[PDB]
Amino acid sequence: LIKHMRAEALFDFTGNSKLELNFKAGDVIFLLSRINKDWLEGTVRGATGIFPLSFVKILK
Amino acid sequence: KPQPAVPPRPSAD
């Protein structure tokens, strides 16, 4: 699993199921894995799930 | 700013 990497949400994201990670613009998401070209997996707000790469920017 | 479109979800159907 990925360690020490984070992304910041650029927009709010409300998922379609509990497999998807909900967040608000500005939230910092702790990255865990990459699902495919368009989706990442991470944790924020106590939950773990998938979300779109296009909704975040990777932090330095 | 408007939210971008959501990419197709992973699937096997």
Image (cartoon, coloured by chain):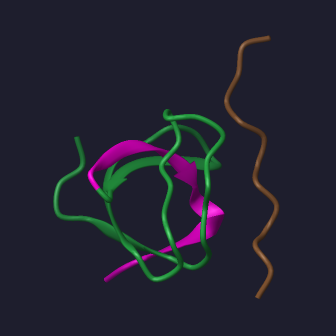
Chain colours: A green, B brown
Residue A33 seen in the figure: no
Is residue A57 part of the magenta span, yes or no? yes
- Residue farthest along the left direction in this orientation: A4
Figure check: A43 above or below B2? above
Q: Quadrant of the C terminus of chain B?
A: top right
In-image side of A2 versus A18 (left or right): left
Location of the N terminus of chain B (image quadrant)? bottom right
Residue A23 part of the magenta-drawn span: no
Question: Does residue A52 appear left or right of residue B9 in this picture?
Answer: left
The x and y percentages for residue A13 are 61, 62
Q: How many marks on residues? A: 0
Q: Measured along the vertical axis of the image, is residue A55 above or below residue A16?
A: below
Does the image show residue A10?
Answer: yes
- Range covered by the magenta-colored residues: A46-60
| Point 45% across, 83% down: residue | A26
User: Does A33 sit above or below residue B4?
Assistant: above
What residue is at 78 percent from the left and 40 percent from the top? B8
